[PDB]
Amino acid sequence: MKEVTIEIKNKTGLHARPAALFVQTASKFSSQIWVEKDNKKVNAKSIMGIMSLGVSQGNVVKLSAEGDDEEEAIKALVDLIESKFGE
Amino acid sequence: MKEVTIEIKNKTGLHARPAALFVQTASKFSSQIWVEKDNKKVNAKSIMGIMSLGVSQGNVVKLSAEGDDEEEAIKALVDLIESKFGE
Image 1: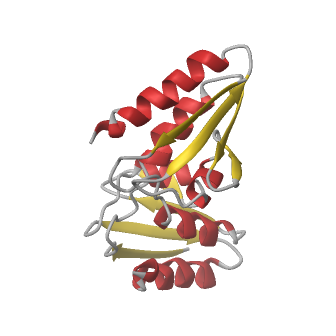
Image 2: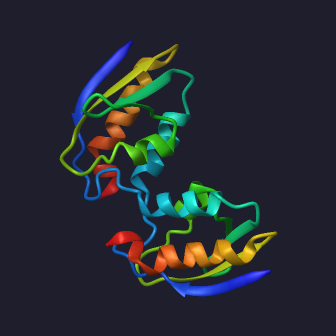
């Protein structure tokens, strides 16, 4: 075994909540969901894609859903987004 | 189908790189890896756990690995951490 206690010194530590509550909400649904930023489409239920979209404060993205609950699911993400996630 | 183009207004947009390059490095290995912050253990290869550890700049965590490459794998995470991920 190999072990180290180390200090996290980068700005946002390991903060990733946004993509967190997002993917959590997006995941609660059966509707397939996508997030498109500048012609880059990614699965809204995948934290990786979200993180890879490099979406920052100020970015406009296209949120799409298609499924038996596509309406309630976008209302969510959108509502979640609109609160600033908290902030 | 339901679609909305919306602006991302929260601070860090959807920025989650840290947990990103971390889990990416941690995932490249066979050694099982853990991240323990204040007696909270989580799989270093799981972005969810990382994000849930609520690790911020300044936090000390315990990094452990156990496997055929446990040595090279901690050197990684540690080296990755030590650069501030970039910053």
